[PDB]
Length: 229
Ligand SMILES: [Zn+2]
Ligand SMILES: [Zn+2]
Image 1 (cartoon, rainbow, N blue to C red):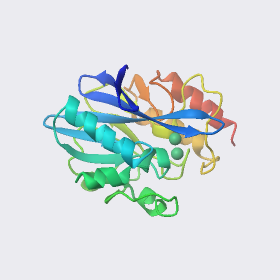
Image 2 (cartoon, helix red, strand yellow):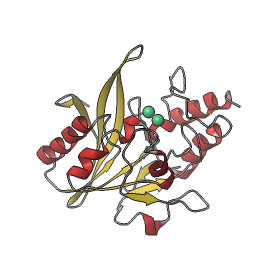
Image 3 (tube, rainbow, N blue to C red):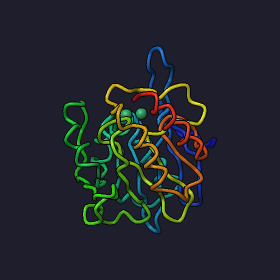
Image 4 (spheres, protein in one colour):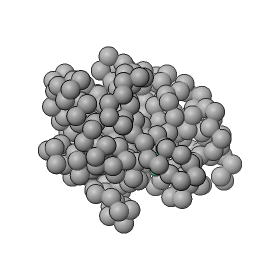
């Protein structure tokens, strides 16, 4: 989106929404982008996903201070992998309340990650139990079922055409589903489709590892995941 701050990139997606992007050198893959979101809700800022590292995550907070200059109220993190929860310490150090799927917090220690302070639980229909997501504002949080990981969750932003698939969703031209080490091969395809069904009005699909795409990204992803079963 062209805003470069330190080693991160910030792209405005809507008047109150930005994508944050951080990079990690992974031999044999290159310098790998990971995307999250920043949302302004009135007088506060909400964050979706950390950067890969604590330092990068501190940089996200520095950008927010400089460009928005409102307090960060809370952060929700999609799953227990380094690109989504690598920077938990920086959020906690800043006094930011953090939230994750209960299962993500249970998985975090063995993954070498810090758990969020708070656990989300999910209803029958996959939607977050409201009582476990206080003050989430426009963030609508949905568990689509196991896919990229057992614990992967997704987030739509109310008042926008934006839904965030995290690492569940790949772009419409992706040549693979990327990392499948912790993937649920049987359930991935249905979980990807369920994400689309939860946010039917979303025309902009934000994801971890490619620039924002149309709903064709969901279509393409589920079709790749089909070949896993
Ligand atoms: Zn992951
Ligand atoms: Zn990822």
